[PDB]
Amino acid sequence: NSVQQQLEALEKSSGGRLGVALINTADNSQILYRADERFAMCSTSKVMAAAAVLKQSESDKHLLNQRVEIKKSDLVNYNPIAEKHVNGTMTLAELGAAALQYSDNTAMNKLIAHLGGPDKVTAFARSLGDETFRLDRTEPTLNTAIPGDPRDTTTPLAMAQTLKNLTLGKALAETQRAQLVTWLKGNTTGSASIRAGLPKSWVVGDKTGSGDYGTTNDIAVIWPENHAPLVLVTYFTQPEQKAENRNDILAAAAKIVTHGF
Image (cartoon, rainbow, N blue to C red; front, side, top):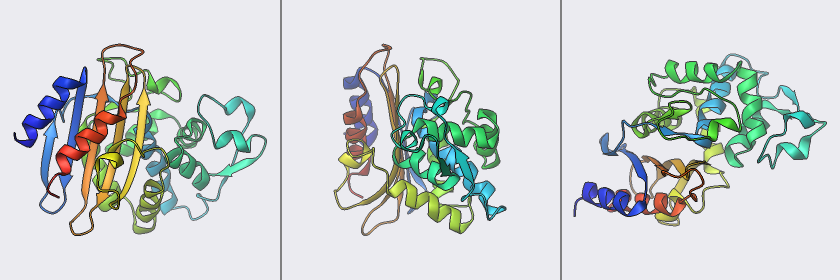
């Protein structure tokens, strides 16, 4: 069976809806499955918020070290880093690191607030040529992931294209690109997702996300040992609100599409 047939069969077994976009940077070839359909991003949107702050830092050499006060009232759900810093400060760089490497929701909200609200994250995506991404809400409500709701969604292809531009391409100046890559490579939350479907020694940078409707996502840049990088988005969502998340599906999809590479 072809790769496409393999993805169809994976989706058929899944009890939900699978979205995959792989870009092989050797030749700009793509493996696309529901790649123009919308999925709730959940925490994968944290990449765009962090990158928007990195863009600002290009023109403000003091920005990344700017102090941000962390107050008890800022805490939401899932803030393993920010809760350590209540009554103190974190820098914008530290908030980027926490948002990306630990998926800290308070850190995400501080980035969004710094930028001036969700719509400013959308504007940043648009400035990179991404016509699809939209951020509408803050944490935690951006994870409701209701089927057919356009809020806080993108498509697998749009996200793969933008992730490529951010990490390997033209979106950010070099120091900021390098910082984003360093952050993604140091992610702690993605062991069981795309990474689990790849050779153990491949270098990977990724950002996971999950939400209601069993929405289970991962976006990654992958550096094989003897090949050009791959950019891979795997999004998955289910019909029932309290469905379990399914990172195993993402690992399985990653294994299918990276075969041979």
